[PDB]
Image (cartoon, coloured by chain):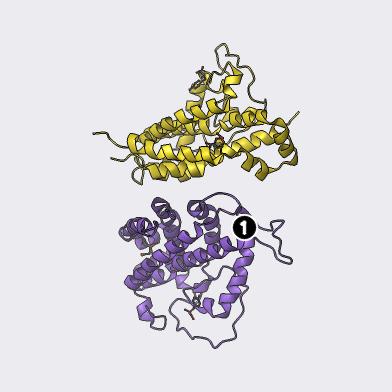
Chain colours: A purple, B yellow
Amino acid sequence: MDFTKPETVLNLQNIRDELVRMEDSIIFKFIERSHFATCPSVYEANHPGLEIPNFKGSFLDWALSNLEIAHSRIRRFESPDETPFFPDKIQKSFLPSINYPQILAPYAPEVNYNDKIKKVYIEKIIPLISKRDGDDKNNFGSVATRDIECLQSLSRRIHFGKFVAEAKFQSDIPLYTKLIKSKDVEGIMKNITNSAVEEKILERLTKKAEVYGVDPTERRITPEYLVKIYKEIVIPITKEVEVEYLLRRLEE
Amino acid sequence: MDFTKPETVLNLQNIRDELVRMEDSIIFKFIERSHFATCPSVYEANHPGLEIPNFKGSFLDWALSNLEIAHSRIRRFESPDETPFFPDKIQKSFLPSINYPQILAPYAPEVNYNDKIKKVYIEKIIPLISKRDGDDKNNFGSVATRDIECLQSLSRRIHFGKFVAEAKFQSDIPLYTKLIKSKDVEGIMKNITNSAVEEKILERLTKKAEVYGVDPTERRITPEYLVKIYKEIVIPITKEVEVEYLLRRLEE
Ligand SMILES: O=C(O)[C@@H]1C[C@]2(C(=O)O)C=C[C@@H](O)[C@@H](C2)O1
Ligand SMILES: O=C(O)[C@@H]1C[C@]2(C(=O)O)C=C[C@@H](O)[C@@H](C2)O1
Ligand SMILES: N[C@@H](Cc1ccc(O)cc1)C(=O)O
Ligand SMILES: N[C@@H](Cc1ccc(O)cc1)C(=O)O
């Protein structure tokens, strides 16, 4: 899957294959985060004791914005598969730009569930991957840099819905246009949903959490929890993206 | 440990013994619940398909509330070791009362972690003990009556912290008095924590699971998941109960 060969990107099989690769990445990251306590204070906005002057948001928010300018600089978000958490806040870098040929429809960057993803990650995901419960007072930074990678992976994967969506739209334009004009939510949804694929996903994840999750000579990840997570969050939201993208697919 | 002989209830060893008998009980209940699936729907609040007239709450909530009034009728909550889930929804019985002498301080009934207990049980425990993943449309009541059973045990056990707390308090009033006035959490926390004791507990659970969990002629419960639960939820929340009890211990 090459980003300057529109064809090799708008290929569903490929797209799924890439998603499969991400499974491990995401796993590895969860595994990492498991080492530290929950660290409530890190996600709590404007925490006294962790106040950063002229800045409003949570320790994590800060950490995430800083990092985003760093990645911003090495041209990260200039890429269609990369969508920033603090979008209206990054600057055009000091580096020639890779001129990625248009694959997705122009408004594509506007679709941005990071607000949701960040939220659900903090509230639903954290309790399931973190070990102890409480504030690990001198690992806030640690915890933070980790939450960020999880978050970025999570976002890449999830925001992949746009490609899938586009790819599918291609496969049957009349059918989709109809549904879209119709603003037929349930109709589109059931058409894009393929329970068989998502069925295999949940199965393999269980196996991976079992091998990677234990010292091969312990238990940094809970198989059932990972399923819970992908089932209740990862897969659901990817589909939200898919439909939202689809509706606006006939704009001017 | 006789509830009409206060001194025998305020003996730390006795309290510990009773907490041991409970291990089996809980295992049994867990073992029972393990026969049915996760059954998501039983937990979803006001589920379209299970809607109960003039009632906001989940199927479980209803099963739980009803059951509580039943036990309420047979004087269940009139005792210091039983703390209800819907505390103010309970009516006094039609039955001459047992007259328990004071053991705990008056505000005791107010210390109530059942919201957390119920919520954690639903999100962390259920996935670990239920066999498969999905809804068993004609076993919701079963799942529900057993969940409640697990719930009442956990609740009894966890809330035992109050007795422990009151005990440790008696053992060295001046020391705790200081910590309380200071409202020194970490100070109380590490002063009431006995890791040798909690270490021994995890040990025998591992074994108990290996024997009760398998048909002596399989695997209703992993000794690993059992250990996980007590370590992450049971013991932790029991300690929360002990701190708060102590903090409020100096009230007028
Ligand atoms: O077709 C697809 O592959 C994509 C991705 C998806 C997932 O979350 O993996 C898998 C199955 C489909 O129902 C949805 C969600 O569209
Ligand atoms: O001393 C105690 O007995 C009580 C109960 C407790 C537990 O949860 O088992 C066991 C050990 C202590 O560290 C805490 C938690 O207080
Ligand atoms: N793939 C692009 C965009 C990118 C940059 C940095 C990243 O961390 C991720 C993606 C590049 O490497 O130029
Ligand atoms: N032990 C008391 C209170 C009690 C009632 C019902 C129960 O389910 C449990 C405890 C009694 O039975 O007299």
Q: In the displayed structure, does residue A73 sit left or right of residue B122?
A: right
Q: Secondary structure at mark 1?
A: helix
Task: Tell me residue B91's x, y (percent).
Answer: 58, 21
Residue at 66% x, 58% y is: A45
Out of A211 and A231, give the one closest to the viewer.
A211
Residue topped by disc 1: A42
* Residue B30: x %, y % from top left: 40, 36
Q: Residue type at mark 1?
A: Val
Q: Chain of mark 1?
A: A
Query: For this view, does A217 lie left or right of residue B3?
Result: left
Residue closer to the observer: A185 or A37? A37
- Residue A75, image x and y in percent? 54, 80
Look at 40% across and 45% down and name the residue there. B224
Q: Compared with residue B161, is residue A242 higher up or lower down, i.e. above or below?
A: below
Determine which quarter of the picture holds residue B225: top left
Residue A172 seen in this snapshot: no
Q: Is residue B140 above or below residue A41?
A: above
Image coords of residue B228 (percent x, y):
45, 45
User: Which residue extends farthest left?
Assistant: B217
Q: Residue at x 43, y 55 (%)?
A: A221
| Ligand 3 within 8 Å, label 1 CB | no
The quarter of the rendering in which ligand 2 is drawn is top right
Q: In this rendering, does residue A29 appear at all?
A: yes
**Circle 1: is it few (<14), some (14-19), or many (20+) Cα within 10 Å?**
many
Task: Using the image as rendered, state which of residue B222 and residue A193 is in the foreground.
Answer: B222
Image label count: 1
Residue lying at 45% horizontally and 81% vertically, measured from the top left: A102
Residue A15 found in image quarter: bottom left
| In-image side of A59 versus A197 (left or right) | right
The quarter holding residue B84 reads: top right
- Give the position of the N terminus of chain A as an image quadrant: bottom left
